[PDB]
Amino acid sequence: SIVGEALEYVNIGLSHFLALPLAQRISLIIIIPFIYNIVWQLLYSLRKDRPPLVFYWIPWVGSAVVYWMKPYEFFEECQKKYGDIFSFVLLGRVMTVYLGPKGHEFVFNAKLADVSAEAAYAHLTTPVFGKGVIYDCPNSRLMEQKKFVKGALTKEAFKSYVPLIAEEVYKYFRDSKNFRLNERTTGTIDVMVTQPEMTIFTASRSLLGKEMRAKLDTDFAYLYSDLDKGFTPINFVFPNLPLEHYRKRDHAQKAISGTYMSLIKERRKNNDIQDRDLIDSLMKNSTYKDGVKMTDQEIANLLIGVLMGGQHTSAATSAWILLHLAERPDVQQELYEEQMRVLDGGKKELTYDLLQEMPLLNQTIKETLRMHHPLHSLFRKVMKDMHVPNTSYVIPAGYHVLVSPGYTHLRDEYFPNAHQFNIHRWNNDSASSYSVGEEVDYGFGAISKGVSSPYLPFGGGRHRCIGEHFAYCQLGVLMSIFIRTLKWHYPEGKTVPPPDFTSMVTLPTGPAKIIWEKRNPEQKIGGRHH
Ligand code: HEM
Image 1 (cartoon, rainbow, N blue to C red):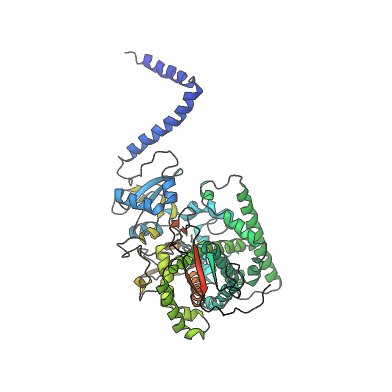
Image 2: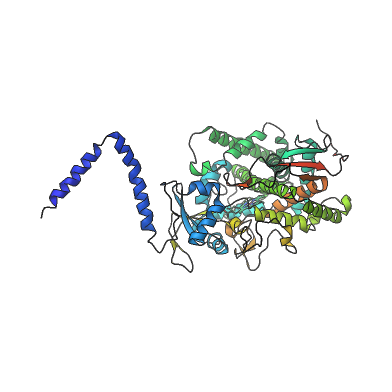
């Protein structure tokens, strides 16, 4: 017995390895991880306590490419091969997807100790919003921040925001080069140009107030653009490599929060603290229950976060509404009749209460949010091994879970002819959402306990959206005025564009152009302008 003579050759083989020509060493630096990764997946598939893992050729990268470009097609293929729960590798991360209403329950209603949203999201949002708020703080702090913000999102606030938002839409029709309704009776617009502008203008005026809205008439508006460019998915992957747009982002966060603090300190200086906007509200109502006050910097940062949370969701949504309606003059016609009925042929000024008597308008918003959920995937990082009910699967800590209610929105089983835009599928069901039973309060108000609805555009559980009613108010006013003022249609041979999922906000693929025409060519919009 001389195995020892073989152990010598292990050592010998090792030294011959280190002496390979650089050409072959490089090749082996490639081939070894490639082979190991394939061997690893084969072994992994034998485990019974793990959901099926989607096969991938390139290590670390995983299924990133296909998930990035066409996530719903990716989900549908995986769902056919493996069923509703499956994992895939995404740039060094393992993502476990749970499709359908049971998936909604598993992720949105997960125990606070099981999963973390801030662990998934903070590296992307913290540099944009600033420190101390949203995901740069314990969940209990987030809960109270949401409570604070909801305090300026009351029915009473919406009654005051509606004429403010309407003024901004009319000003945009009057003054924007995309319209100029006093000078032109027809024109062509790119809805991915107009809607972000209309969105920030209307949200600024109502949530931040007249001063902050005035700032957007200046070069200052470009900081918002800069801040926005630091909010892309490459910041998800590489949170900070010293790139140009990273620093413009940091600069913008400091400059914009600086402007908000300036106004906050000015208002406190003059005791000019009213009930006009979210700034007034947070100045009066931002003390945590342990008695610690939000700093002025944190208040400013939270303002940025709130405006940002409403910016891309709403802008994408009003863009899709215009795009679906552009090939549906029958739906424009039907919405126009409702406007004439509810507002007495235009004789009534639009109010928040009359908005609630516009079911078809609200069903249009509801249906667009069904077909175009602006966030195709929501994430949590798994913090404790999770057992998946009625399976033998365990999702270990360190994995991520991914939930996609927008995918379920597009399934025939839950919405017949799911790829058909039909506002009447919501007849006698025009509410933005509603708790279909028992409620629960995580610290920012009573919300639905069950999150099993196949329709979940605002998510659910502790991380549930609080901007839903603001969004309906904003989109409601905006679409009410579009409908009463304009008709619109596609250029010849154009139709509803397919979604672009790469910004991870489900935008229409540009350029998404429509042609508008004034319903009343001679109608003038009053007020002064240069
Ligand atoms: C069409 C409009 C909107 C849609 C579809 C939408 C969607 C969502 C969704 C799906 C979530 C949950 C994310 C998750 O669970 O990971 C969420 C959370 C949230 N959104 Fe919205 N949103 C919209 C508008 C707004 C507006 C207008 C605001 C502010 C005025 C806002 C602020 C927030 C906030 C503060 C959260 C809580 C985040 C958390 O607790 O982690 N959103 N939104």
